[PDB]
Image 1 (cartoon, rainbow, N blue to C red):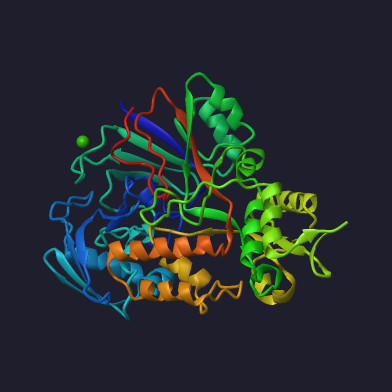
Image 2: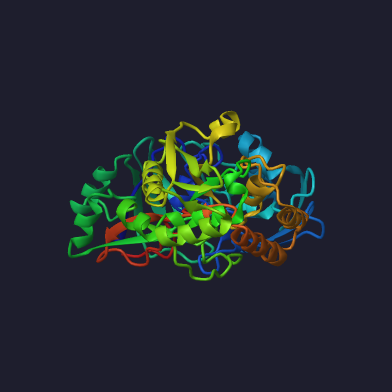
Length: 475
Ligand SMILES: [Ca+2]
C-alpha cells in the first residue's frame, strides 16, 4: 500500500473551503479552483476552467471543461459551478467583497458573469483557494467537502488530522498513491522530530536551528522556494532627506542583501532585486549592482552630502528614524544591521520598535524608513499591490508617493483587461520604480520543506503555497 503522511504548518477545525482561510481543502487535494498559478511560467492558467474572455472587464465569459466530475461522481457543469460560487458569496463576506459579482447566468458549460463594475483583475481572484469549487448538494461542509481533487475525504478530526483516499476518476489522472494522512502540528520542532523519528514523510516549515541537523541525515532532503512576499525598507518621501533620488539610491545600498540571507535568514531566503520575483512574467532584468558602505558614500556625495569631522549637507546632520516591529522577528534584526552600517558612514539612526503599521498614518510626521513586508503578487497579479502602494489614492500609500509618470502607468494598468498587456505595464511600473528607487527591496523569504528523500517522489514546493498534495506525488 502507497501512503504519505504529510505534516502541516497550521491547524483548523473546519474544512469548509469557503469559511476556512487555511486553504487546507486545496492543500490536501480535496478541492480545486477555476484557475491556478502555473508552476512553469508563474502566470494565471486554466485549471477547472478551459478559458475566459472579457471585451470590457465587466462582462466575463468562462467556458469550463466538459470532462470533470466531483468525487461523488456528479457532473461538474456550469450550474454546479454557479451553485458553488453562490454558496461561497453568501457564506463569506471577504469572498463577497473581493469577487465583486453582480450576476451569474449559466448554460451547459459556459458561464456569464457580470461584476458590479469593470473589474480587470477579476479572473485572478478565482485562484483564491477560497473559491474552490465543491458540490453544494452535499451538506456537511465543516467535515466533508466534496470537490474535484485527486483525494477524497475519508475521515476528519478537528484540530488534528484528516484522512484521504485516492479518487479513482479524478479528471486529470489518478494518483498512484493509495492514501494520504494530512495532519497538523503548530510546533516547529515537534515537526522536525516527527520527520526524524520517521513518524512523518513530509514536514512543512521545519525548525530553523534544527534545519542543520536534519539536512545532514543520510536520507532527508530539504527543498526551499521563493514566495511572493518581499521584504523591504519602505521610505517616507514626505521627508526632505529622501526627496532626493541619490539619497534613496544610497539607502538602497547600505544593507548587504546576501548577509541578510545568511546571517539572519540562515539561508531560508533569497536576494530580492525588486518587488517581484524573477520567475514572474512581468519582472525586469536588473543591471547587476555592487552595494556596500563604500557605494553609499558615492551616492550620498552626488546628492550633496559629505562627512565632516557626521554626514551633512550645508549645516544640518544627515540622519533617519527607521521604524521596525515585532510580528516578524528578522525585521528588527535588519533594522539593527542598518543602523550599524549607517554609523560606519556618518549617520545616526533612531530605531523605534513600533507595533502595527497603523503608526505610519498616526505618527505620520517623524519617520524616515520602516523595515516592512508585503506579498506583492498574491496570485500572479500585481495590480492591487502597485495601486495600493504607489498611486496617490492608494490605500496603503503612506510614503506620500506621487509621481505622475508612475501614476500614468498605474492608470492605464487599472483600465486594462488583457493579460499580456497587464504584464507589459507592470514591468514598466517595476522598471520605473527601480530607476526612481522608490523603495529598497531586500529579500524574498523562502518556504521551506523537508522530506524523506527515499520514500517520497515528485514533491514540488510551490510558490503560491497553495499546492502541496497533488496527483503527481508517489511513494
Ligand atoms: Ca477503488
